[PDB]
Image (cartoon, rainbow, N blue to C red; front, side, top):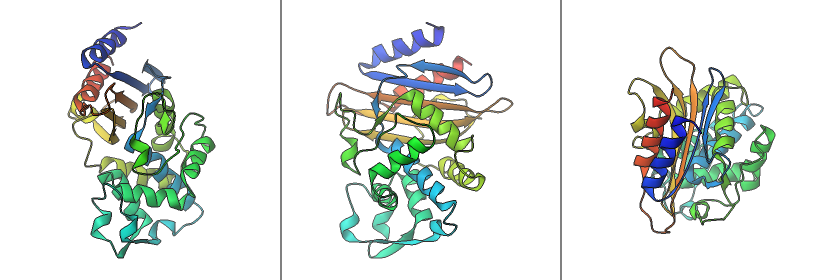
Length: 262
């Protein structure tokens, strides 16, 4: 096991929880993995999968992203920073996607899942782009229970890293759709203390964080350093106690160790 793995293991040991990491360096398409085939609760990182799936729909429904969508009181769940600004109005599928990705709005996520026909529709998109591991079983907010051993609403670091590559750098999506996803990810406003805090300041990052129960603290990101090929980094972390506190620092520190390993 390499140098980077010894440090990740020590990081993990100092944390008292369970850490999962997967990097894809698209130079020699090299990978660095730590518990990369273990399942982790995705929490709000799953919003990328749902937004990407609506994007893929819009390829043949050219005006789908402009379709207005009613926001009714009953649609509000536990955390709706944007949607609560439009109760008894509308938001378009573009505004809903942006809200889900940029402000982690759970009502926005639920509208994307409904557009796709339920959680099974998000899983179907994953299968349709090669990802046999991702599974979305519940809507917001119950997908965040992150119960140890519960396979619901999980993926693996290896799987999500490859998937995120295909979506943001490959051609799982039409170019137009891919560019809109990148824009959305770069304009995220909620994942600054995680991966973003362990990387060189000058690298560009688009990412999506996720928290839930059991101190689950996650981040998935596509990174553009200067002078070299882009990379994909996934960092998942979860803890033994249901009421555990968030540990974004562990994700930043894993990102630091990975980048120090380039």
